[PDB]
Image 1: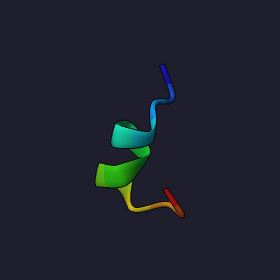
Image 2: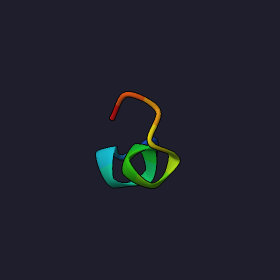
Image 3: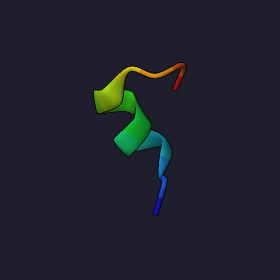
Length: 14
């Protein structure tokens, strides 16, 4: 859930 790895792929200021 909204994990850092998910934001990593999104490259949205992970």
